[PDB]
Image (spheres, each protein chain N blue to C red):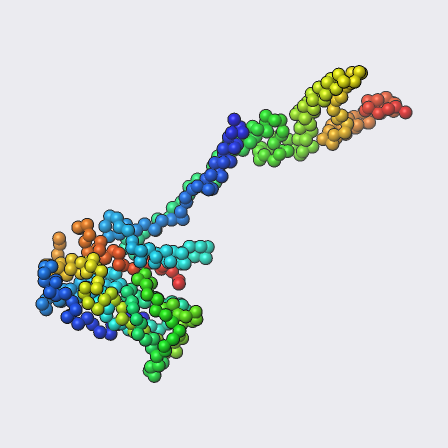
Length: 182
Length: 195
């Protein structure tokens, strides 16, 4: 399980013209330092970037929930071998769109099996929308409340409002209570 | 009053098994603020990981990793047994005290008073059955003798009651072992016709 992303965000899709109004190479260096700080706390994606979840063993036989939460259109399920013949499979599973648990529910059967050495990888385009105007606005507001902090103070210095950064991203974090075996 | 305690202390526990909330615990979610509810996308996730992985007999001991803000405070149920237990038994023994039944015969759980049912049944047919029957049959004897001419007597027959056999065998062993008096003199001591 790696989940490295395919393509980074272009920077033309980030609202550097809107962030300037709220407060270009230094402004855009602070939104994506605040987009990546909010996604890492909320396990979200916010810009619909492409990913590659390359994992070695399926956790269940009708599961392996995806960590990046808002998903749509799993592109492929490439089932590689050790030498890398790279034969993709095209049937057997279903992307089940769910903000709670984005999972691969399969089709009433065990998920595609993995060769000895050949790690199965999933490429999917997960996120809210391709632009900035497609986000939930409070999660878009939480980026501006954090990126304006990184702009207005440079080192780790000192200064809680009712709906702050933490109170706006408390409802996008993954609420999990299983530290168990399954 | 002892009926009203035994009815109510038994309807105490009937109600308490029908309207009482004990939880096994509570998953407290305060949030980033001092308070904050969790979203329906998060409440559907929290149930599915509580239903599937943490409830039941087959999930008794899962670690339940708790993030920042989440918390599991397990509730107890501190008076579990014995809600009015020794007062319901003390009331159920005062009901048997009024009617005159000993607590062995109906099965009330209590410190043993009689020993082995040979004397619990013998005290029952001597303190509260045969005094009650010798008053009902004596009123039958006088009232029904107002219908026929001759006055009639009608009283309980202790000879044909199996609870007085422990009374009867120590009688028959008393004058049976008394060999000084003759055979025709001990038939009359037992209510037998001399032959």
